[PDB]
Amino acid sequence: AAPX
Amino acid sequence: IVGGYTCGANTVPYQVSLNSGYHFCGGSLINSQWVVSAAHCYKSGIQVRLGEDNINVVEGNEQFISASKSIVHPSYNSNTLNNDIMLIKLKSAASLNSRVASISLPTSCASAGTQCLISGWGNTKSSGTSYPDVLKCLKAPILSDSSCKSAYPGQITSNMFCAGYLEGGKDSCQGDSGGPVVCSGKLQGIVSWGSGCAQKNKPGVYTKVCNYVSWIKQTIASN
Ligand SMILES: [Ca+2]
C-alpha cells in the first residue's frame, strides 16, 4: 500500500 | 493512469496539474478560486496549472496560478490516509471558459457499479515507470464496499471507496494522486492510494468526496  | 487512453486536449476541463517545478499531483477545479486535491499532495510552493494537456509544452489555453492557501483536512492521518483531502485557493481567480471549467460537487454519494472517469498525468506502467506528456483517462466503476474491504482488510474507512478492476491492468497510479473521479458529472472521488497500481485483486482507493461537501463549503466560506 502506498499513496498515489 | 495504467491501461487508459489519451483523453484529448481539454476534454477534462476541471483537471488541474499541481506543479513545483515538475508535475507532482492532480486536482479538480470546483470554482474559479478553489481546487480540491489530496491532503498527501500538500507542500509549499504549489503552482496550479489549468487548461493543460501536454504538461511539457506551452500549447495555448494554459493558466498558471500560484496557490495562496493550501488547507489540509484537520483530521488527515498520514499513515492511514483517512481524510485524504485538501483545498487550494488560487491567488487570483481563474478565467473560466470551455477549456477551464469547474466540476460540480456531489449532492449524494454514488452507488456500487456507477461508472466514473478518472484522469491524470501519472505513471502509465504497472511495473516500472513511464510518465506521459498528455492527459490520460480511464473509465472505471465504483466497487462494492464488501469487495473493497476484502481487497484491503482493516484499511478502508468510511471516507474511502474502491474503484477499478480486480483483473489487473487498469488503474490510477503515482502522479495521479489528488486528481478527479467524476461520476455522472459530480466529483465523487479523489485519487488517494492503493497497493501498487493495476495489480490483480488490488483496486484503487479514493477519498469519498460526498462526505466532505459541507466541510468544503464551510471552509471556502470562511477563507
Ligand atoms: Ca502545456
Image (cartoon, rainbow, N blue to C red):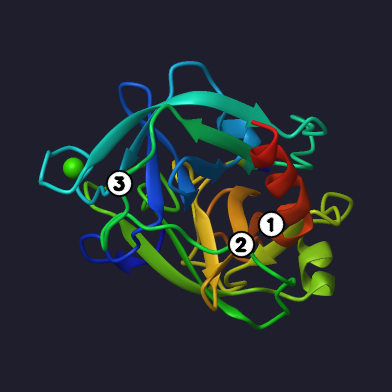
Report the residue marked by disc 2.
Answer: B105
Q: Are marks 3 and 2 on the same chain?
A: yes
Q: Residue at x 10, y 46 (%)?
A: B59
**The N terminus of chain B lies in which quarter of the figure?**
bottom left
Q: Which mark is residue B86?
A: none
**The C terminus of chain B lies in which quarter of the figure?**
top right
B92 relative position to B41: left or right = left
Q: Position of residue B94 (x, y in %)?
A: 35, 42
Q: Can you tell which of label 3 and label 1 is closer to the viewer?
A: 3
Q: Residue at x 36, y 53 (%)?
A: B124
Q: Residue at x 76, y 46 (%)?
A: B215
The answer to whether the residues at label 1 and label 2 have Cβ atoms under 8 Å apart is: yes
Q: Give the quarter the ligand 1 occupies.
A: top left
Comparing B12 with B204, the one in front is: B12
B168 relative position to B208: left or right = left
- Count of picture labels: 3
Circle 2: element type: loop
Report the residue marked by disc 3.
Answer: B95
B158 relative position to B99: left or right = right
Comparing B189 with B214, the one in front is: B214
Instruction: Tell which subunit mark 3 falls on.
Output: B
